[PDB]
Image (cartoon, coloured by chain):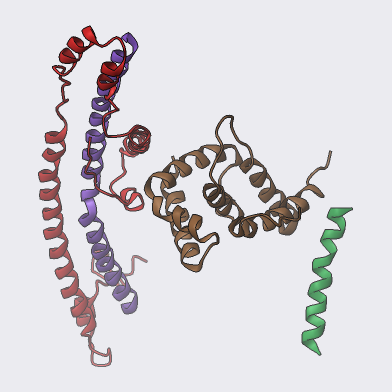
């Protein structure tokens, strides 16, 4: 569980940065 | 074709000049040899004083 | 005690080692490369640093230096099997050739910008020279 | 005893000619580090030989006084260096080789400078004829006789 949920946070942060930069 | 020839000549000159520098600092090896042999020789000299003093103390 | 009685210099390098080991323990036991491989690569190095011999305690500043070398990542390339020899040789060399540096840390009680500048050069040079 | 050694840069030390000498340098690293560690371990000053006064203070002092008189007559030899001349021997040969290398390299550099200067000065190819291009660069020849093209086909 630690590994699997360590993997997704990078994608979520990258998409947050892209969304905020876009608008 | 002409430009390529120019590049080749420049590369040869730079290679020779670069190789000149490394020759200058060749002195370091001899210093290492000298220091190693001198220190190694003095180390055994000190132990003799230590040995003689200890041998003297035990007898008393 | 909450580290109320502890030298200022040691806190800087120990508070950061706490997090490294806490995050190493929660993942690196399974009876990717971006996060997981680096995490246990650092953790296996950090574990080996804490081993010690018998009848030979150390002064505080030497521990500060040896932990400072590990925490900053200067030893993330060497194979973990050879860390102890590096520790011993580096400690002997630092004790002999750099007696003035330790007194600065002992007297001040904390690290400084000049001290931090000196330590990186010393560590990189000795690491380069120490490959045997 | 007192020592006067020379500080070295091992990073540049590895740059010196290592061919067929890697093993020698590897041994030298061990010797240089270990001998320094051993020297630092023991004090250079001689140990405390003040026991003779203690022996006088010690109740058993009488014949020990004669033995101390013998003790003051003790002498310790000093080893003599033998490899010092051998190290100095190779330096002259290395210096001669370096001088020869410098001379040859400088001659080659001057020749290359002349050739580069020749290459830089060049006609803009509009006034050039076929022969002058053969002068500047090697080009076709007449080895394939009885041909209207001479291209090696």
- Chain identifier, brown in the render: C
Evaluate whether residue C77 shows in this view: no
Q: Which residue sits at x=26%, y=29%?
A: D46
Residue D97 pos. (x, y %):
13, 49
Q: Colour of chain B?
A: purple
How many discs mark residues in the rendered view?
0
Residue C41 is left or right of residue B54, and the answer is right
In this rendered view, identify the residue nearer to me: C21 or A7: C21
Q: Hey, which residue is sitting farthest right in the picture?
A: A1
**In the rendered image, which quarter contains the C terminus of chain C?**
top left
Q: Taking the image as drawn, is residue C70 in sight?
A: yes
The structure residue drawn at horizontal position 33% and vertical position 69%, both measured from the top left corner, is: D151
Q: Position of residue C117 (x, y in %)?
A: 47, 64
Q: Quadrant of residue C103?
A: bottom left
Q: Is residue A17 left or right of residue D135?
A: right
Q: Colour of chain D?
A: red
Image quadrant in which you'd find residue D148: bottom left
- The colour applied to the residues of chain A in this rendering is green
Q: Quadrant of residue D48?
A: top left
On screen, D52 above or below C15? above
Answer with left or right where residue C69 lies relative to residue C103: right
């Amino acid at each position: 569980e630690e590994r699997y949920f360590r993997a997704r946070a990078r994608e979520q942060l990258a998409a947050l940065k892209k969304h905020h930069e876009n608008e | 074709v002409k430009q390529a020839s120019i590049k080749q000549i420049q590369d040869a000159i730079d290679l020779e000049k670069s190789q000149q520098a490394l020759v200058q600092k060749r002195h370091y090896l001899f210093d290492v040899q000298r220091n190693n042999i001198a220190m190694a020789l003095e180390v055994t000299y000190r132990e003799r004083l230590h040995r003689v003093y200890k041998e003297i103390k035990n007898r008393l | 005690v909450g580290s109320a009685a502890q030298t200022r210099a040691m806190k800087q390098v120990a508070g950061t080692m706490k997090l490294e080991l806490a995050q190493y323990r929660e993942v690196a036991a399974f009876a990717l490369d971006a996060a997981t491989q680096q995490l246990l690569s650092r953790g296996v190095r950090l574990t080996e640093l804490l081993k010690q011999g018998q009848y030979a305690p150390m002064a505080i500043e030497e521990q500060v230096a040896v932990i400072y070398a590990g925490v900053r990542g200067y030893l993330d390339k060497l194979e973990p099997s050879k860390i102890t020899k590096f520790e011993n040789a580096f400690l002997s060399h630092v004790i002999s050739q750099h007696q003035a540096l330790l007194g600065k840390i002992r007297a001040d009680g904390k690290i400084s910008e000049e001290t931090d500048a000196k330590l990186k050069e010393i560590v990189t040079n000795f690491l380069a020279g120490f490959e045997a | 005893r007192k020592l006067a050694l020379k500080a070295i840069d091992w990073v540049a030390f590895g740059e010196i000619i290592p061919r067929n000498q890697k093993a020698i340098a590897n041994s030298l690293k061990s010797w240089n580090e270990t001998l320094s560690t051993r020297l630092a371990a023991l004090p250079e000053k001689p140990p405390a030989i003040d026991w003779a006064y203690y022996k006088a203070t010690v109740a058993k002092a009488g014949l020990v006084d004669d033995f101390e008189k013998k003790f003051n007559a003790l002498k310790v030899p000093v080893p003599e260096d033998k490899y010092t001349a051998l190290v100095d021997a190779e330096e002259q040969e290395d210096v001669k080789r370096c001088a020869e290398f410098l001379s040859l390299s400088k001659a080659r550099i001057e020749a290359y400078e002349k050739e580069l200067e020749k290459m830089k000065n060049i006609i803009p190819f509009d006034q050039m004829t076929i022969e002058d291009l053969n002068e500047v660069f090697p080009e076709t020849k007449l080895d394939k006789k009885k041909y209207p093209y001479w291209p090696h086909r």
